[PDB]
Length: 529
Ligand SMILES: Cc1cc2nc3c(=O)[nH]c(=O)nc-3n(C[C@H](O)[C@H](O)[C@H](O)COP(=O)(O)OP(=O)(O)OC[C@H]3O[C@@H](n4cnc5c(N)ncnc54)[C@H](O)[C@@H]3O)c2cc1C
Ligand SMILES: NC(=O)c1ccc[n+]([C@@H]2O[C@H](COP(=O)([O-])OP(=O)(O)OC[C@H]3O[C@@H](n4cnc5c(N)ncnc54)[C@H](OP(=O)(O)O)[C@@H]3O)[C@@H](O)[C@H]2O)c1
Ligand SMILES: O=C1CCCCCO1
Image (cartoon, rainbow, N blue to C red):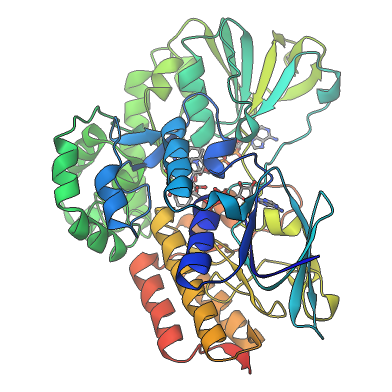
């Protein structure tokens, strides 16, 4: 039983920064934990081939330390998993953080002790810590989703989830199946196709994707970025999604067809999924006709790329362009390869997995050495629901969030005093590092304020929390993303109640809300002295 000021759960971007603020700016005794053997979070787990950010390299990082920003370098316009991991290990060493963390150590329970006004946190090695504050940075795309298939456990080959890819494992020369064609599946398929002996893709919902445009960067282009870094970050912080481009306000149907095509073509040539969805016109996410113009443009490209009409039919995206926008380094062109087969599982479902592979309902065995599951995540709330977390009077997080998960401001919830979340439910949907920093900075200020002012507990009221839920819901219902049927609204997991899970007002609005709450003496919080 060690006693400390603060516990941080997670050693991704969130947890790394939170330990830094709580320790060096607030002078609090702070311990961090990760199940992982080192820092990096997402970029520690997802070592699958092709893993690559869709935020441009110069913005997928911390902004808080002006010297670090001048020191870091990168090879290309987007940054790969090993490069991000190295960046994060460098942050941890640069700021002497490593000593706060217990790696290979899962937090298994966190229990609030009403009389003592402390959290009791236990690890899977039986260590017990008591803390005044808990900061949860457990990842909104971290709890793996791994569907059961009939017969899966008779399979004699290897099975791998992409977000648990063992470092070093290569599938070169093997016969491989991939289940999943979201952001991960596209990357893994594109990068496996040239090295595997045969690839079979099991596609349930083909998605819309545009080119990433990942180009080599020399040490000069990067010099110009580094020379304007202050303004770069100021604009990012004052945009909606903080991806580094100007979010358009131009309505798509207010220009001619010719011009519309030209604007989409320029975005397509330039690259980037978010730029396609938000850099071109201002209403692709809120107006049906604007959505359909963007969708048709992409469908027409698929048609020109994939040469076999039957293959193209199976890969043709349909319906609203309303999932997380995807981009790729040659995904659709993979299906022109003779060692790649697409299996459209909505029309030819999986019958079962047997010793040697996957059998479809047409009676064909797809013979496979390895099955890769790019089946995504129990997003946002999944890592909370899996830990034993109990608040005031032993209320379990799963009974508190008995239906949808909720927060006040994305960083707190009622009945859990002195307990904060980084990227909890109902927070911003943006390039995430600058949102993580907004939240960590705001939590650190709040804890600092509590310590200075002798506050014993802070927690949001149920009224404020309900208002925040309603605000998220209203903003969501004004967009088409409601009908996209993906992880973003909890619709990807059998047994998960679909719900709003994000505040979609953008980083500029989010930051203004957060700063006003703090300037106003923590409006919506109950504060006990
Ligand atoms: C393949 C991939 C690509 C992505 N690309 C982008 C992108 O381009 N742009 C973008 O903005 N976002 C992207 N994301 C989202 C990305 O997760 C965030 O950018 C960011 O890495 C989140 O960092 P985090 O610290 O909040 O959580 P994570 O990096 O998910 O770290 C959470 C950590 O908590 C640990 N943990 C959880 N529960 C426990 C427990 N009980 N005890 C101990 N440890 C625990 C986990 O092991 C994990 O290491 C991507 C995600 C994935 C999976
Ligand atoms: N920066 C990047 O380039 C990058 C890369 C990877 C991940 N990410 C982030 O991580 C998020 C999640 O991405 P992801 O691709 O891992 O997950 P995802 O978008 O949730 O996609 C999961 C895929 O698995 C399929 N699937 C799920 N269950 C299945 C089942 N039982 N049988 C057959 N198919 C099944 C889904 O089909 P349906 O659509 O039919 O459900 C979908 O194609 C992304 O949206 C993005 O935010 C980003
Ligand atoms: O890939 C990501 C993570 C989901 C939320 C913002 C979009 O960028």
